[PDB]
Image: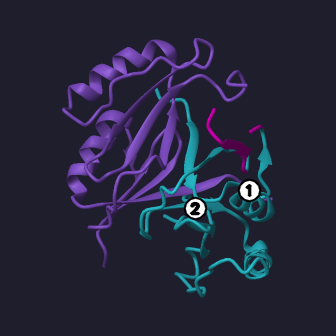
Chain colours: A purple, B cyan
Amino acid sequence: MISGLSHITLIVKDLNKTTAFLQNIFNAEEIYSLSKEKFFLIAGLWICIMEGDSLQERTYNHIAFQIQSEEVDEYTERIKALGVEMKPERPRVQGEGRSIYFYDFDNHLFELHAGTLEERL
Amino acid sequence: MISGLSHITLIVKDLNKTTAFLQNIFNAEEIYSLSKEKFFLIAGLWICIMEGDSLQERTYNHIAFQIQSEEVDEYTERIKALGVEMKPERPRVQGEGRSIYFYDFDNHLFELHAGTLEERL
């Protein structure tokens, strides 16, 4: 059996810049910083960031984090207030919960979803 | 606080084909199958697969799953035995554990790593 997820590794052009973004929105705790890179825990999740022009084009391939209903509006606020790229919010299926999509500086699509797979069925 | 991860969504050209791959290697349990898509649990992990030519180029952006030391060789075997693209294995820091990298059919890089972030520091 595969244990769980080990980590997600993401490649970004500016390190420091992505960092502030992460610890601002996702509130990542850094673990530490040869080759320039940094580790983070986001919602107990091992995220690794490596510097590099590896940012090929925008796709629907994305990571969704679980937030909670009341948080959606507050989180919308935060993302806007960092001037990060944030799509307008579409209503799903009033029983499928809400989602917000926004990018980091490096073509990375993020979703904040609210409403468990469990109920999502 | 962000709860955990909600799900990772991946875009693949052939659905059925990716599927077999997933449930073969990662042993994903399907949850179910408008628009063609399928859900899976991989190591208690909500993975969603959507059909689409959205497979922009190969990068180091990747997902690593946690496996265990003894499994490494067996898992190497499996990946080879599906004829999926698998990089040759590099020894890391004899105290940083081992890793294996391989692609799905759609420029998706996967890592199977063995050895906790905890000890990885």
Instruction: Tell me the subunit letter for badge 1.
Output: B
Observer-nearest of B39 and B117? B39
A113 relative position to B37: left or right: left
> Where does the image place residue A23, in percent across and percent down from the top left?
32, 40
> Where does the image place residue B44, in percent across and percent down from the top left?
73, 44
> Where does the image place residue A98, in percent across and percent down from the top left?
50, 20
Query: Is residue B40 within the magenta segment?
Result: yes
A16 relative position to B83: left or right: left
Q: Mark 1: give few (<14), some (14-19) or many (20+) Cα within 10 Å.
A: few
Observer-nearest of A18 and A31? A18
Q: Is residue A89 above or below residue B89?
A: above
Q: Residue at x 57, y 64 (%)?
A: B119
For numbered disc 1, what is the local secondary structure? helix
A20 relative position to A27: left or right: left
Q: Is residue A41 above or below residue A100?
A: below
Q: Which disc, if any, is residue B64?
A: 2
Q: Residue at x 50, y 35 (%)?
A: A65
Q: Residue at x 36, y 49 (%)?
A: A108
Q: Quadrant of residue A120?
A: top right
Query: Is residue A92 within the magenta segment?
Result: no
Q: Which residues are magenta?
A: B32-42
Q: Residue at x 32, y 30 (%)?
A: A87
Observer-nearest of B114 and A51? A51
Q: Which disc, if any, is residue B1?
A: none
Q: Which disc, if any, is residue B16?
A: 1
Instruction: Tell me the subunit letter for badge 2.
Output: B
> Where does the image place residue B80, in percent across and percent down from the top left?
74, 82
Disc 2 marks a residue whose amino acid type is Ala
